[PDB]
Amino acid sequence: SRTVITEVIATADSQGRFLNSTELQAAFGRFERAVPAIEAARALTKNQDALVKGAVQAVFKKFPYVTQPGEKGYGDSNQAKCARDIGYYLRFITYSLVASGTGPLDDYVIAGLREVNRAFNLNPLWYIEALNYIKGETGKLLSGQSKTEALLYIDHAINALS
Amino acid sequence: SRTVITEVIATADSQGRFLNSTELQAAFGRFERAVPAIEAARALTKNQDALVKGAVQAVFKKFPYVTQPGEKGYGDSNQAKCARDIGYYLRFITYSLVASGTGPLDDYVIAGLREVNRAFNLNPLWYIEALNYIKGETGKLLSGQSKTEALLYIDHAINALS
Amino acid sequence: SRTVITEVIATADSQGRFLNSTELQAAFGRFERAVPAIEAARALTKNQDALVKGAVQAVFKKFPYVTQPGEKGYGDSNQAKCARDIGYYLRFITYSLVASGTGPLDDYVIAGLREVNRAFNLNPLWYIEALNYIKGETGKLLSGQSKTEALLYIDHAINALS
Amino acid sequence: MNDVFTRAIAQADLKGSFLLESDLDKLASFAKEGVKRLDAVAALTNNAPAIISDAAHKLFAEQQELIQPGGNAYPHRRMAACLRDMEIILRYVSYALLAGDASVLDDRCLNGLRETYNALGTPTQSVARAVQLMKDAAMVHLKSTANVTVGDCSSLYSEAATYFDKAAASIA
Amino acid sequence: MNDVFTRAIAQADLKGSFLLESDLDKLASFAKEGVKRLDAVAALTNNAPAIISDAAHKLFAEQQELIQPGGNAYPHRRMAACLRDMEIILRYVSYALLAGDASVLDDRCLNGLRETYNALGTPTQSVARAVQLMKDAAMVHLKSTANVTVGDCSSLYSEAATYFDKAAASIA
Amino acid sequence: TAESQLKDGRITVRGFIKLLAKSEVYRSRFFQKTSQNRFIELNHKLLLGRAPYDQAEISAHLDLWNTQGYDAEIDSYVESEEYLENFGEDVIPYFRGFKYQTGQSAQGFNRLLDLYGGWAGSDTDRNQSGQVARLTNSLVRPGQVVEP
Ligand SMILES: CCC1=C(C)/C(=C/C2=NC(=C\c3[nH]c(/C=C4\NC(=O)[C@H](C)[C@H]4CC)c(C)c3CCC(=O)O)/C(CCC(=O)O)=C2C)NC1=O
Ligand SMILES: CCC1=C(C)/C(=C/C2=NC(=C\c3[nH]c(/C=C4\NC(=O)[C@H](C)[C@H]4CC)c(C)c3CCC(=O)O)/C(CCC(=O)O)=C2C)NC1=O
Ligand SMILES: CCC1=C(C)/C(=C/C2=NC(=C\c3[nH]c(/C=C4\NC(=O)[C@H](C)[C@H]4CC)c(C)c3CCC(=O)O)/C(CCC(=O)O)=C2C)NC1=O
Ligand SMILES: CCC1=C(C)/C(=C/C2=NC(=C\c3[nH]c(/C=C4\NC(=O)[C@H](C)[C@H]4CC)c(C)c3CCC(=O)O)/C(CCC(=O)O)=C2C)NC1=O
Ligand SMILES: CCC1=C(C)/C(=C/C2=NC(=C\c3[nH]c(/C=C4\NC(=O)[C@H](C)[C@H]4CC)c(C)c3CCC(=O)O)/C(CCC(=O)O)=C2C)NC1=O
Ligand SMILES: CCC1=C(C)/C(=C/C2=NC(=C\c3[nH]c(/C=C4\NC(=O)[C@H](C)[C@H]4CC)c(C)c3CCC(=O)O)/C(CCC(=O)O)=C2C)NC1=O
Ligand SMILES: CCC1=C(C)/C(=C/C2=NC(=C\c3[nH]c(/C=C4\NC(=O)[C@H](C)[C@H]4CC)c(C)c3CCC(=O)O)/C(CCC(=O)O)=C2C)NC1=O
Ligand SMILES: CCC1=C(C)/C(=C/C2=NC(=C\c3[nH]c(/C=C4\NC(=O)[C@H](C)[C@H]4CC)c(C)c3CCC(=O)O)/C(CCC(=O)O)=C2C)NC1=O
């Protein structure tokens, strides 16, 4: 996965050289940037189910027709598996926080997203604004330094969906 | 040249996509300790005369054969050239420090060093020993993080020469 | 600012006559009370930082459940402001000790307390437990009289919180 | 592809003398406001699709001939090319902003870009209007104080406006 | 390619669950003590010629039948390839030391090396001996207290030794 | 960006091949997860349409990489006279090793067969094995077979 450490190593590897000053510079930046990110991951993980419920009900409130009979949100399976999808997005945002890179997002979600959304007719907007709800909720769930990191990854997910 | 911002921008432009979390984190890691680098460059730009004369005399001491007539070390213009060479190396170490990367060091000293050195019949161990003395005295003129940055950059120059 | 002499003045001026035996005797009594309270307040001003910090950690220890994500106090700034709150109340304890009355307390903090707590969702019981910690130490720190009126003042403070 | 540090080193080596005290001090300052710079470029990156969409809406509203048949942005292919050029321009603007130097923009994004549009028949005036509307939207998204600590960044807004404006001038 | 963080993440994802509190504690400790790791990686990077040269000296002073004619390091091309392999293995050990995970080593240097050395006739026992000699020369360099603050790094010594032993046991 | 460059015509198809070879997809698949032997095999197969002819090719390209980096390693393939004569600026590379190409060894055909793996198969690296090298012993022991 593409992180700071891995990107450093791959760059110093493809060039066939040892790790010089700039590479250890970036590595150190990652290592001390870790602690806010780890705390953000702990908070998001602790507040996981509440965040998922909130994002699901935000999808339904903003997209009221979706739960009406005959289309996507109708029926219990599609709601339970909406919860599943939001849980996946949240899990990979925390993964990307811990790794301090957009590796896990760009691998397990962003890579191959448009094809599977197209082939299942899943509107991206549902996920974009569920991520917007989580983006807002981290404002009162986190604060300080780690809030910028969490917002940054929620943000990258939203941009990739759009 | 090649500074941390330079690789960040180059890698971001290569994929043709905006700067994500990792690039900003790398730029932050460069930015936050720009100050030990700049203060180290300031500390070793005041002592440049002492540095160059010490390096030249240490090179003369370590290699007695490069002193007596019948060789390149002997000579008033040749010793002026030696002092100018050491001044150039130290100035490019300062440039590497202020850039917070190896870029100016690379594309002023390291690139095309072997054949340029060879076509004029100059021993690499000469400049290696000069930079070793610069290492020795910058270990004491600088303390802590600035000392770390110095040691690392001068040794990168040495490894390039060696 | 209703120190005992202040309501003496209020009772005197409310009607037309000068000060009789009772208020003069009460003023005398307060004027010997002034001393042991004054050493009590001085002793507490000597022991500021250790006592306030220990009160803060006692609040953590008796209320651990908040310490999780869920404190209004969670985060360095909020814990520090817990400490400054305890410092403010210690200020007012000392001031009322000197004033020989609830003057500072009821004038500033007791005035409009409950609705402020409701607005800011700050449970008084935390403060009460902090003052019970203060009870524990002040049982040793002060002796005899100074101890007695200090305890009585912080009893009135507890009751104000309730 | 130069930043302020590489550029300053270039002039210092052109002179041949060591770096002074004052310039090194202003470089240290640049480092200190580097965090506000990173938040500026982050604000630009975070909202790139929104900026492109709103600037495109306004631009196509102001010049209806672009959309109508025979216009330069009529078919879906040409509209997609327009939006992609807008995004590339904004991407290089953010690149220059983080580098703190306009060199990143001019050295690769603006060399043959000026005449390619003319050879294509593309009106460069419309491109200038597009990047101007982009500049307006980027300013709006930059002055936002939500989710970030507040402080003085007027130099950053002026620098971003200069980058957008010289991109407009060089394209035009 | 991997590191410690991505390894924990991959395990958790294959299982399907968020990262537990204990694993977050482990990664936080790793990141907290990673400054010593940067010092070790620098000790390997900066002295690498010394390691390679001392290991070569010892290997060819104990195993003469490599440098003999008909030995498999006889001409300058084979000796240069020997030294180049030594440097490359040391390079991937420093990589894996920075990453904290030996996946880059096992994927770029070690996944086809025993077969290559057998197909070339090079005695993989001597290659493993060279790797162990490099380990010894490096440990002389990672324990250097000059130019760094005093502290304990027994964990990093053990980790680097295990990386060298992985290279040795996957070549031999 | 590369596709836009190609559509405008600032780069020929060969330059676009060069950009894709230096891209991060090509690295992450063929370089980063594989030894140097497998990387050279894949580079020959993908940028030249042929398998390696002998061991000196592997030695030369490994030294070229170790001394000059991935970009020079890739340039040695695309700027080579062989690519320019076979495919030139404007032809997409294809598997030309199936029909006798002038100068090839006898083995190049067998090695390309070993690399091919069918029309369905691919140079994935998502296998259970992890993109091992196929021609390690067929190049230095072209004829014989040895058991450990
Ligand atoms: C790696 C992470 C990952 C993601 C993100 C993911 C998304 C995903 N969602 C799917 C189905 C679905 N997803 C939804 C989501 C909707 N449900 C509610 O109504 C909301 C409006 C909305 C969610 C906000 C729905 C309705 C389906 C069923 C549609 C269908 O069966 O065609 C499917 C098809 C497979 C299946 O679930 O049967 C995928 C692949 N899958 C993954 O493995
Ligand atoms: C900024 C880039 C730069 C570098 C790196 C540099 C080194 C350098 N020094 C030179 C001359 C020289 N340099 C030396 C010094 C060496 N011989 C002994 O005296 C010493 C032991 C030893 C120094 C430690 C000497 C004697 C010459 C005389 C001409 C020659 O030997 O080629 C030359 C040949 C051309 C010239 O400058 O006159 C180069 C390239 N010059 C540069 O402009
Ligand atoms: C003498 C007048 C005075 C009073 C009455 C006082 C209490 C007080 N507590 C406040 C909020 C707060 N008070 C606390 C401390 C409490 N929360 C934790 O749970 C602890 C258990 C507990 C400490 C005993 C915290 C953490 C906040 C921040 C909550 C917020 O900003 O909404 C505020 C709002 C102003 C601010 O944000 O600093 C005041 C004025 N401070 C004073 O100077
Ligand atoms: C080559 C031929 C061609 C087509 C077909 C085309 C589609 C097209 N329709 C547009 C406007 C639009 N068209 C619609 C109509 C949709 N919304 C609802 O009314 C309906 C369900 C549905 C149509 C039946 C809407 C809502 C917009 C405005 C989109 C927006 O400004 O965000 C736009 C954006 C133009 C602008 O306002 O800047 C395009 C590109 N463009 C072309 O050059
Ligand atoms: C890892 C990548 C990264 C992030 C996430 C980041 C956000 C960030 N903003 C900061 C402070 C700040 N950031 C700003 C800039 C903002 N203030 C105004 O609202 C402007 C509109 C706006 C400019 C776009 C200001 C003024 C400060 C406080 C002054 C200072 O930095 O010392 C700080 C340092 C202190 C802190 O807030 O804890 C960080 C790390 N910086 C980074 O390098
Ligand atoms: C640019 C690349 C870079 C380097 C070179 C770097 C070195 C570096 N080493 C440090 C401390 C240290 N360095 C070491 C390592 C030494 N002590 C052990 O006894 C051995 C002799 C040896 C390692 C085997 C230790 C143990 C510490 C203190 C651990 C800590 O910081 O908590 C520190 C923090 C200052 C301190 O807390 O004392 C730095 C910045 N950081 C970087 O970002
Ligand atoms: C090096 C940086 C770079 C630039 C500068 C760039 C611009 C650019 N725009 C192009 C086509 C185009 N460009 C536009 C956009 C313009 N026409 C409309 O009127 C708009 C008002 C206006 C946009 C603001 C359009 C509509 C086309 C389609 C013309 C065609 O397909 O032939 C092309 C050729 C075809 C292609 O891209 O595939 C280039 C190279 N691309 C780059 O990689
Ligand atoms: C990128 C990671 C990677 C590595 C490092 C690697 C090793 C490697 N070593 C090789 C040859 C060699 N390797 C050695 C080294 C041995 N000779 C002595 O016995 C020593 C004990 C020992 C070295 C310590 C020698 C002498 C050759 C040349 C043999 C020949 O030319 O036939 C070759 C093929 C031909 C050549 O390089 O000239 C490879 C591919 N392969 C890879 O994919």
Image: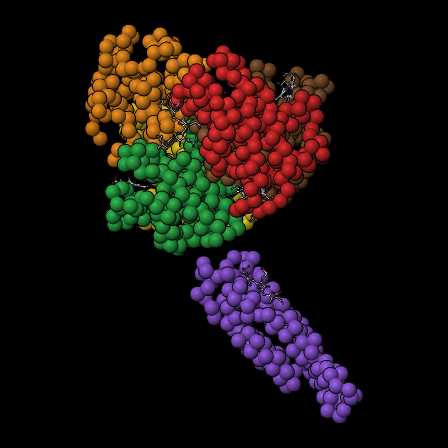
Chain colours: A green, B brown, C purple, D red, E yellow, F orange
Q: Which image quarter: residue A88?
A: top left
Q: Residue at x 34, y 11 (%)?
A: F91
Quarter of the figure that contains the N terminus of chain C: bottom right
Image vertical order of residue F47 relative to residue A45, above or below: above
Q: Nearer the viewer, residue D94 or E18?
A: D94
- Direction bottom: furthest residue: C21
Q: Position of residue B131 (x, y in %)?
A: 61, 30
Q: Position of residue C69 (x, y in %)?
A: 45, 58
Q: Residue at x 51, y 64 (%)?
A: C121
Q: Nearer the viewer, residue A53 or D57?
A: D57
Q: Nearer the viewer, residue B42 or B32?
A: B32
Q: Position of residue F5 (x, y in %)?
A: 44, 18
Q: Is residue A90 left or right of residue C102?
A: left
Q: Residue at x 53, y 30 (%)?
A: D134
Does residue D87 show up? yes
Ligand number 1: quarter of image? top left
Q: Residue at x 33, y 38 (%)?
A: A123
Q: Is residue F22 left or right of residue E152?
A: left
Q: Is residue D155 left or right of residue D115?
A: right
